[PDB]
Image (tube, rainbow, N blue to C red):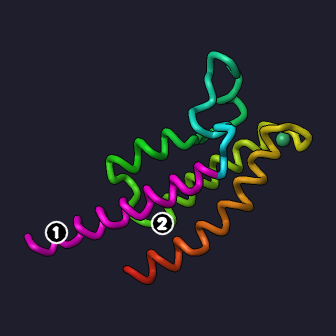
Amino acid sequence: SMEQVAMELRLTELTRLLRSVLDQLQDKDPARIFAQPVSLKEVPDYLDHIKHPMDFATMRKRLEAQGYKNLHEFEEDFDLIIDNCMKYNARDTVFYRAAVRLRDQGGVVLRQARREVDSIG
Ligand code: NA
């Protein structure tokens, strides 16, 4: 149906916007602390601590399968990246501090992204 096609065109346009949002968020992590999943080879106990791991590559795989239906879903995953890090790592570490910085800087990007997704519908 044409109704189905139009919904698919909306999903595709959301995906295009979320890709640009994701590039912008990832530029706020120049050290690439959040680029890849935490390795279970190098933190074997990780899954005893963190129930829902997340990272930018896993977000990008989901994005390219057009697996985000709205901004809320994408934000949930971004927040997991930050929130997992701040729980596993202590306040005085380079990791926790990189999470704080990504959060603060990412908040700006997401503030306007929420306006653009509303605005363009
Ligand atoms: Na902690």
Establish whether ligand 1 lies closer than 8 Å to the Cβ of label 2. no
Residue 5 shown in magenta: yes
Q: Quadrant of residue 68?
A: bottom left
Q: Earlier in the sequence, mark 1 or mark 2?
A: 1
Residue 68 relative to residue 108: left or right: left
Give the secondary structure at mark 1: helix
User: Given the current orientation, which residue lies at the most extreme bottom position?
Assistant: 119
* x, y percent for residue 84: 70, 44
Which residue is pictured at 66% across the width and 52% down the height? 28
- Vertically, is 18 above or below 2? above
- Kindly identify the residue that appears in the image at 65 percent across and 30 percent down: 47
Q: Nearer the viewer, residue 107 or 47?
A: 107
Q: On screen, 119 above or below 30?
A: below
**Quadrant in the rendering for residue 41:** top right
Q: What residue sits right under mark 2 in the picture?
A: 71
Q: Residue furthest top?
A: 41
Q: Amino acid at mark 1?
A: Gln
98 w.r.t. 37: above or below: below
Circle 2: residue type: Leu
Name which residue lies at 63% across and 30% down: 38
Percent position (x, y) of residue 80? Answer: 63, 49
| Magenta segment | 1-27
Residue under label 1: 4
Asked if marks 1 and 2 touch (Cβ < 8 Å), the reply is no
Q: CA distance from mark 1 to mark 2?
A: 20 Å
Taking the spot 52% from the left edge, 79% from the top edge, the residue there is: 115
Give residue 79's position: percent from left, percent from top: 63, 55
